[PDB]
Image (cartoon, rainbow, N blue to C red):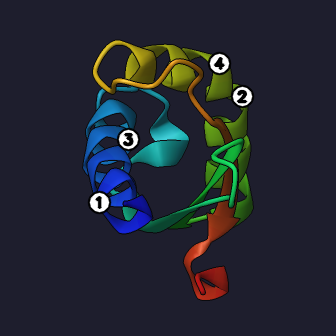
């Protein structure tokens, strides 16, 4: 189901973000993810160490490379696009 795919995507994305070198992402962690009803978009809730806005911009800028990274490890015909939000916003 949905909950299981979200767990796989969360662990996968947390690892792919850790693989990025952007200093704005230092010590950033992924608190949760939520996929849209149809799987079109994955909302990713993160906890930034400093300058939360800067971390969100860094992830947003890396969105295409991150989706490419997910496509290499998750089996989905079309991977969801990513929306990055502050951890306080998680459902």
User: SS of the residue at dot 3?
Assistant: helix
Residue 63 vs residue 74, the one in the foreground: 74
Q: Residue at x 43, y 61 (%)?
A: 2
Q: Which residue is mark 4?
A: 64
Alpha-carbon span between mark 3 and mark 2? 15 Å
Q: Which residue is mark 3?
A: 13
State yes or no: discs 4 and 1 in contact (Cβ < 8 Å). Answer: no
Residue 86 vs residue 37, the one in the foreground: 37
Q: Nearer the viewer, mark 2 or mark 4?
A: 4
User: SS of the residue at dot 1?
Assistant: helix
In the picture, the quarter occupied by the C terminus is bottom right
- Residue 71: give x, y in percent of width and height: 43, 17
Q: Quadrant of residue 59?
A: top right
Alpha-carbon span between mark 1 and mark 3? 14 Å
Left or right: 72 in relation to 53: left
Q: Above or below — where is 44 with respect to 8?
A: below
In the picture, the quarter occupied by the N terminus is bottom left
């Amino acid at each position: 189901g949905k909950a299981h795919l979200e767990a796989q995507l969360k662990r996968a994305l947390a690892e792919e973000i850790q693989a990025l070198e952007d200093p704005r992402l230092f010590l950033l962690t992924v608190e949760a993810v939520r996929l849209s009803k149809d799987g079109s978009v994955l909302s990713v809730y993160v906890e930034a160490f400093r300058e939360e806005e800067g971390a969100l911009r860094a992830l947003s800028r890396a969105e295409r490379r991150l989706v490419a990274a997910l496509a290499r490890r998750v089996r989905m015909r079309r991977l969801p696009r990513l929306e990055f939000l502050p951890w306080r916003a998680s459902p």
